[PDB]
Image (cartoon, coloured by chain):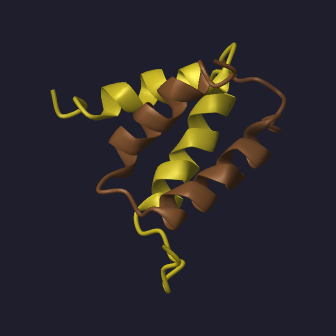
Chain colours: A brown, B yellow
């Protein structure tokens, strides 16, 4: 349970957008906003 | 719909932990991991 790699792929871009959203609409809460925004991202293509 | 501030409070620390989790357990997916980890954070205190 130690691992030898420390580079989260697709983590930068994804997070980046976050700052672009939470700021373009400063939500009343992040935790909840993170679950709603991401929970939907799974069905984005829809 | 423009806003004049650009500093998400409580956003750094929160995100920081993320990198500490997604890396200490490289999940099979971030989006879903973001919704599960955060969706639960709301009931953390529990």
User: Looking at the image, which residue sits at the far bottom?
Assistant: B4
Please indicate whether residue A5 sits to the left or right of residue B41 in the image. right
Rendered position, A16 above or below B7: above
The tally of labels here is 0
Residue drawn 57% across and 32% down?
A: B21
- Depth order, front residue of B1/A40: B1
Rendered position, B22 above or below A11: above
Please indicate whether residue B10 sits to the left or right of residue B22 in the image. left
Please indicate whether residue B27 sits to the left or right of residue A23 in the image. right
User: Looking at the image, which residue sits at the far top?
Assistant: B28
Q: Position of residue B43 (x, y in %)?
A: 22, 29
Q: Position of residue A8 (x, y in %)?
A: 78, 36
- Depth order, front residue of A10/B23: A10
State the image quarter where residue B30 is shown: top right
Rendered position, B6 above or below A30: below
Residue drawn 68% across and 31% down?
A: B23
Residue drawn 49% across and 37% down?
A: A37
State the image quarter where residue B39 is shown: top left
State the image quarter where residue B6 is shown: bottom right
Rendered position, B43 above or below B28: below
Q: Position of residue B33 (x, y in %)?
A: 55, 22
Residue drawn 54% across and 50% down?
A: B15
Q: Position of residue A16 (x, y in %)?
A: 70, 54
Q: Quadrant of the C terminus of chain B?
A: top left
- Depth order, front residue of B4/A32: B4
């Amino acid at each position: 349970h130690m691992g030898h790699i420390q580079i989260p792929p697709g983590l930068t871009e994804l997070l980046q957008g976050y700052t672009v959203e939470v700021l373009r609409q400063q939500p009343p809460d992040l935790v909840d906003f993170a679950v709603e925004y991401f929970t939907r991202l799974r069905e984005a293509r829809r």
